[PDB]
Amino acid sequence: HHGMASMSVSTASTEMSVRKIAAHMKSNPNAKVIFMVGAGISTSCGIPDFRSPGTGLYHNLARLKLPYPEAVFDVDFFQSDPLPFYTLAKELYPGNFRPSKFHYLLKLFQDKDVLKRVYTQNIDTLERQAGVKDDLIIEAHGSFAHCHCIGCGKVYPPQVFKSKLAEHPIKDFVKCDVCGELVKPAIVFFGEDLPDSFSETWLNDSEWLREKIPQQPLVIVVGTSLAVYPFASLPEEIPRKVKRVLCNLETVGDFKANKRPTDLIVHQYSDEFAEQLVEELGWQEDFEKILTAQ
Amino acid sequence: GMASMSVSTASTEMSVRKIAAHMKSNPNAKVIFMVGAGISTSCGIPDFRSPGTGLYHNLARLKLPYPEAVFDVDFFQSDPLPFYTLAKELYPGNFRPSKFHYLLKLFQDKDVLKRVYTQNIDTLERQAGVKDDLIIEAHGSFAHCHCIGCGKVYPPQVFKSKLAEHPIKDFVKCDVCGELVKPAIVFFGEDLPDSFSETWLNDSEWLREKIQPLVIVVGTSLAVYPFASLPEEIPRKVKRVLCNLETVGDFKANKRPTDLIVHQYSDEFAEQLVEELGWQEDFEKILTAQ
Amino acid sequence: HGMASMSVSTASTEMSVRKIAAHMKSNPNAKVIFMVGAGISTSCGIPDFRSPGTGLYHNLARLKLPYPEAVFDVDFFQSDPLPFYTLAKELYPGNFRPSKFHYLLKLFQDKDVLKRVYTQNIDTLERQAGVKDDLIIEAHGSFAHCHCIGCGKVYPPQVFKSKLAEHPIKDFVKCDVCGELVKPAIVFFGEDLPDSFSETWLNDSEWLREKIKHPQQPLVIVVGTSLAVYPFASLPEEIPRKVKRVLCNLETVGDFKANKRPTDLIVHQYSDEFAEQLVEELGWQEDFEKILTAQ
Ligand SMILES: Nc1ncnc2c1ncn2[C@@H]1O[C@H](COP(=O)(O)OP(=O)(O)OC[C@H]2O[C@@H](O)[C@H](O)[C@@H]2O)[C@@H](O)[C@H]1O
Ligand SMILES: Nc1ncnc2c1ncn2[C@@H]1O[C@H](COP(=O)(O)OP(=O)(O)OC[C@H]2O[C@@H](O)[C@H](O)[C@@H]2O)[C@@H](O)[C@H]1O
Ligand SMILES: Nc1ncnc2c1ncn2[C@@H]1O[C@H](COP(=O)(O)OP(=O)(O)OC[C@H]2O[C@@H](O)[C@H](O)[C@@H]2O)[C@@H](O)[C@H]1O
Ligand SMILES: [Cl-]
Ligand SMILES: [Cl-]
Ligand SMILES: [Cl-]
Ligand SMILES: [Cl-]
Ligand SMILES: [Zn+2]
Ligand SMILES: [Zn+2]
Ligand SMILES: [Zn+2]
């Protein structure tokens, strides 16, 4: 048997967890899956996460001589001193890296029509570079598609700011030609509001989920410490009747605070988790193809 | 009163003192225990999840695909040997009850035991003298066997004798549906015994009806459901006790003001609780008798 | 910096102390409530109660008690007061000087920015630092006077204190109107806290509720306490969600470890260091050093 009241353990090995997830999907064909990801799914691509000990970005910014680590991405600090961010802005642009196996899994799930959405906090855009349709990607923390004035919010093309970085001697910084305030790429900083698409789309997918509880859906959170708001408030807003999966090196956020009987916590690396899920779903072939094509 | 200076994080000595006090104030009140592997560690049976020593961390000679494969119904169905191989050591018999098990017997004698919900299959509470009507084996036992297919029940001996056979030839099958037959102990994926959900359903009301009760949880990491849901389902108006080496489950998440948490080994806990209750005599006699 | 903007729950210390000072700057004239425990007097040379090895409860072996907290339990006291008497001698205030954190409360007072200080200490150190009695709530009593554990009659201190000098302390002080034992008004487990505690909090809670038009936004700061004792430990949880909480302690505890609110500002610093750092971020280094020197 495998009823909702059958013996089970929340934290399980990758092998068992993937069997549970695979079983659910086979039992709920047509159902979709909502993913919520963070810097974790990009470490293997060569991009260190933010808060992991020793290797985290917030542990390798001594060069910037900042008052505190997170200052590089805080508007308050940006207004009073943009040199540091400019100095780091370079490496932040997409391009230098290739998607990971986990990023491609989202693509696979799309090709199999089981991806409902991907709320990401990353700005490396690897989820799109992997094949996922914009319609399905919710870049919760903005991106470099454009820039904006931190004063009135005027929107500008990338090129201008991207230019100022080139020139070594960082002269006066890009100002807003209409209010005179500082202009920067549209990646959310501490202090700023997230884009509209984020809270609006979530508002839609939340009713979608409530509608389903039909072929039951799943929500899978991976590679994030759920330490940043308002993004970290999503997992707890998932209806209790909707199964939640957490594939992370460590149990965090709502999974740690208010673990539910039906929760699935998997302490695994996103790529290993991705590999094992594909096999069990029986989608090795299609996945292999998607991987070789890139 | 109730809104006076009180702890929520006291020392072991004080906590034991308060538990005993509670019982003395409510002489007719009974207790409900909720136990796990932790109470049979001293008997020589290591628990399941403790770092390094835990059973799941020592299944190497069984060459499993993953730790919980042995007690997973899906793996068993497609490959029963590892369980057959491990089932030999799991059969009750080779051990004797711990001082804590006898504390259960002691409470029974004193008409203070309402129920004992256990997740152990070692049957040590039974071997300690606790009446069957007061014991609830939430995770089953080796008392009988059953078919993983149609649920039909059979006696123990056929499966137990097959274990004696060295190269386990053909595995026991159900003579009606042909599916595999195994001891009636709960595996991952399997539903629990009716007595569990049904007795709790009942005992729950008994509690809400008596609001003076006490529910003591000991020796379990509360990682396995639906058993793990038991603690939080205790009425807020009921005093909960947790005797475990580490704060776990609903005691760690939604801690309650009146919650007593004792970080102690169950045997010492019992040895000490017996002291504060002033029952040193009968207890020592029971330890001798059995 | 809207109510739904991007923020970190696990901010570093620098950012945390930064956010606090900023909140006060963008909310001048708003007051702050302090909730404190043994932690803030530790640097003064007064051990707290539960710190591994050094806490008081780990050092009463000589008193041969059934349990540590027994010296401060009415049930045990009512049956055997000798242990407390034996200890009581060294509990009386007056042998220590306030800590920098303590003077930090005074500073906050001078700036007319201190609403109240709920304290579980009985060292009277917030008072010795200059905090007005009306702004101080001693949730766990004091040695100001004594009382009968039976009828509750109040008595002057001296009668109980002199009784402590007598080499072989015998015939313990008793209520001359009911016969029960008398002791200094410091709260023991089993006893009801002083009336003003629950009542002042009843008002301060309404004050908080009425600050959330647009009144300057308050702030509740808890520091130096493990939140192991009720009803005090219920205060930080009874704080309205729309009011920021700050926890300055060596470790996260109470409602901060349990139901941590996104907005909570957790800081693992020694209370004295927290004071110095907060004073700097506030630009009050001058008014502080003068208060410190003038002591
Ligand atoms: N290969 C991996 N597989 C799975 N999890 C991983 C892996 N590598 C690291 N992790 C886990 O992923 C998490 C990474 O956490 P963070 O650094 O905090 O990243 P993220 O949560 O997305 O950070 C949120 C946000 O904070 C801002 O600083 C920034 O703006 C960003 O979007 C950690 O909990 C870590 O253990
Ligand atoms: N002497 C002791 N006294 C008190 N607590 C103890 C003692 N020894 C160990 N413990 C604690 O008891 C708990 C035992 O945890 P588990 O291994 O997880 O055991 P238990 O919860 O009962 O496991 C539940 C179930 O999981 C299945 O695998 C199995 O089927 C079983 O019934 C741990 O948190 C451990 O620290
Ligand atoms: N310099 C310091 N700065 C910050 N925190 C400190 C410092 N020194 C100790 N601490 C922390 O302060 C807390 C002290 O906790 P307690 O001993 O429990 O003290 P307190 O909470 O006030 O105890 C409450 C009450 O319990 C009774 O026993 C007694 O009556 C008392 O008022 C601990 O969490 C400890 O790590
Ligand atoms: Cl759909
Ligand atoms: Cl819900
Ligand atoms: Cl209830
Ligand atoms: Cl509220
Ligand atoms: Zn502008
Ligand atoms: Zn059958
Ligand atoms: Zn009296």
Image (cartoon, coloured by chain):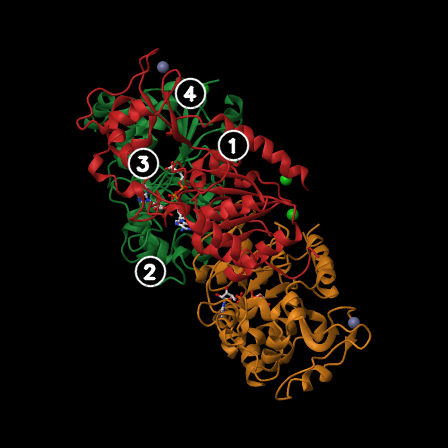
Chain colours: A green, B red, C orange
| Amino acid type indicated by mark 3 | Leu
Q: Nearer the viewer, residue C264 or B96?
A: B96
Q: Which residue is mark 3?
A: B90
Question: Reading the chain from its start, which is encountered first: label 2 or label 1?
Answer: 2
Q: Which residue is mark 1?
A: A240
Can you identify the residue that label 2 sits on?
Answer: A64
Chain for numbered disc 1: A
Instruction: Judge by depth and name the residue closer to the eye, B283 or A192.
Output: B283
Residue at x 53% of width, y 41% of height: B231
Percent from the top left, x then y, of residue A14?
A: 30, 35
Quick check: do tags 4 and 2 share a chain? Answer: yes
Q: How far apart are the alpha carbons under marks 3 and 2? A: 60 Å
Q: Secondary structure at mark 3?
A: helix
Give the amino acid type for the residue marked by disc 1 in the picture.
Arg
Q: For the residues carrying marks 3 and 2, which lies nearer the camera in this image?
A: 3
Cβ atoms under marks 4 and 2 closer than 8 Å: no
In terms of image quadrants, where is residue C118?
bottom right
Do badges 4 and 1 share one subunit? yes
Q: How far apart are the alpha carbons under marks 4 and 1? A: 17 Å
Say which mark, if any, is on residue A31: 4
- Looking at the image, is A17 positioned above or below residue C290? above
State the residue in front, B272 or A188. Answer: B272
C-alpha span from label 2 to label 1:
44 Å
Q: Amino acid at mark 4?
A: Ala
The amino acid type, in three-letter code, at marker 2 is Leu
Question: Which residue: 55% across, 55% down?
Answer: B279
In the rendered structure, the residue with mark 3 lies on which chain?
Answer: B
